[PDB]
Image (cartoon, rainbow, N blue to C red; front, side, top):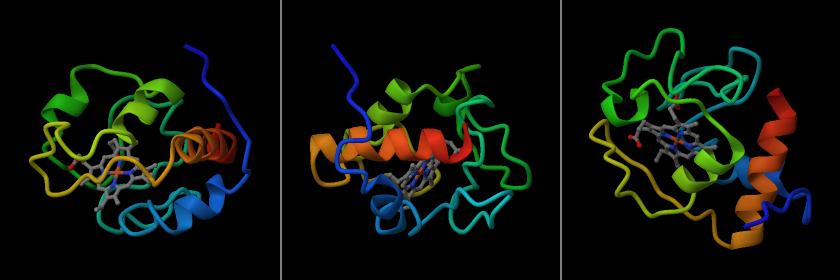
Length: 108
Ligand code: HEC
């Protein structure tokens, strides 16, 4: 199906009230609870510096796409976390679309 993008243009504030709990997108920002996400799309599944998490499912030599990330940002946990905690849907569908886009443009 289509991916929609920059609709509410709240994504960057959604992040601040969703992801900021656990992560940053600042330039090599602090690995607060999970790692920083700077250029996470243009990286792979967790070639984060520093934060040597377990991330077996994550790794599976995977790339991060707006889709793949949106899925990881959609389902309430279940994505084999182990590590600790995943949360899923921000609150709405269009929010996820917004978020992914903003966090795309933020660092890709
Ligand atoms: C703390 C409760 C978290 C919240 C809220 C968010 N994330 Fe997260 N993320 C968290 C952990 C512990 C992990 C490792 C695997 C697991 O589910 O336990 C992750 C993983 C990611 C990843 C992939 C691997 C990485 O290098 O980080 C990404 C790309 C990611 N998380 C993004 C992300 C975003 C954008 C969030 C806000 C919507 C977000 N996470 C919330 C813990 C937590």
